[PDB]
Image (cartoon, rainbow over all chains, first blue to last red; front, side):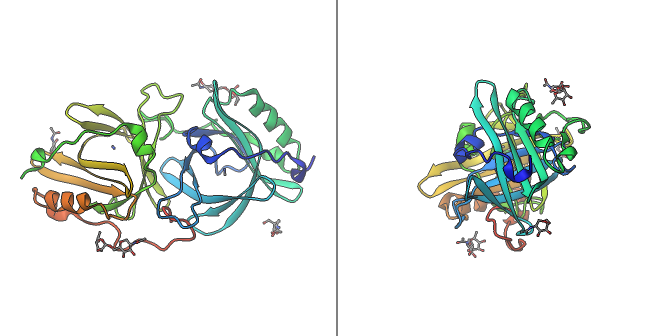
Length: 162
Length: 162
Ligand SMILES: *[C@@H]1O[C@H](CO[C@@H]2O[C@@H](C)[C@@H](O)[C@@H](O)[C@@H]2O)[C@@H](O)[C@H](O)[C@H]1NC(C)=O
Ligand SMILES: *[C@@H]1O[C@H](CO[C@@H]2O[C@@H](C)[C@@H](O)[C@@H](O)[C@@H]2O)[C@@H](O)[C@H](O)[C@H]1NC(C)=O
Ligand SMILES: *[C@@H]1O[C@H](CO)[C@@H](O)[C@H](O)[C@H]1NC(C)=O
Ligand SMILES: *[C@@H]1O[C@H](CO)[C@@H](O)[C@H](O)[C@H]1NC(C)=O
Ligand SMILES: [C-]#N
Ligand SMILES: [C-]#N
């Protein structure tokens, strides 16, 4: 299995992601998205793209990406502080169930997987998430994939922020 | 007029704030909330307070506050990185109109105003907002109140983030 042969699942309507807020990452590839919370935001009333935005929040640091749909269930991200573009797909989504929401998304460079984001609001308890992670580990560079929450700072009275 | 005599308006249901996302600050007191975007978030499925959260985002920095209602239309904030508490009120809200949403909120220390946050998603065009700002300037230390967007960094293809 190479990264380009991973499933490219249908991307749910943006409101379903917004209604899943807040999410935490369960499995990631680089260290970047360890101990990170994800927030989806509707487009600004003044946005001329009318692209919604994904926010990745790690303590007091944040990265934001406006994004639009592309071909074959792709998401095309624009990192808001640099203008750099990324192309993302979903392995699966399972949003707004009785046990909350989960998904796994990935970014490829050809046959190699370069980033991986398994997110949930149910502490990783959707069987689909462990299962999708075991599959993504099998593609080239998927050996980097690991648990995102082994060493997170202690809270000071909030739950998705620190 | 002293800060303690400012109106303490009724706080809209949290979903109305969430449906106003994203907001930008129009007038502020300290420099802290210049060029800042505000995002409201529903409580985490795993939160035991079930407090929603306000996020203030200024470039790649973020401060988060879980908050609950208190007496007399107060909001009681818990800053998520420190645990420090703040008590906030609203001068007015005017959310989810045909011209979008606005509000002005403030924090007092007795008769003195110590922070001020006028927010909107309509570029400050609600007549109530200019009007409320002119009133808050009249309370002690309200002379610090100023336009929040005179010198913000340039965008890189997003609209509420930079
Ligand atoms: C959340 O889950 C933690 C342990 O469950 C882990 O599940 C997978 C993802 C592995 O990374 C492995 O570490 C564990 O089997 C708990 O330690 C933690 O207390 C749980 N939190 C709540 C709120 O239940
Ligand atoms: C947004 O508004 C800007 C100027 O309007 C300002 O209104 C008050 C709040 C004062 O601070 C004063 O600077 C101005 O009267 C415009 O420069 C800007 O282009 C406007 N943006 C859009 C998208 O219309
Ligand atoms: C895939 O490989 C690396 C990723 O940084 C780079 O050399 C190359 O530009 C990428 N491919 C394309 C078509 O951009
Ligand atoms: C109001 O004034 C300052 C704010 O930092 C401080 O000395 C004092 O603790 C504040 N009042 C109360 C009751 O905390
Ligand atoms: C991108 N979801
Ligand atoms: C606090 N709104």
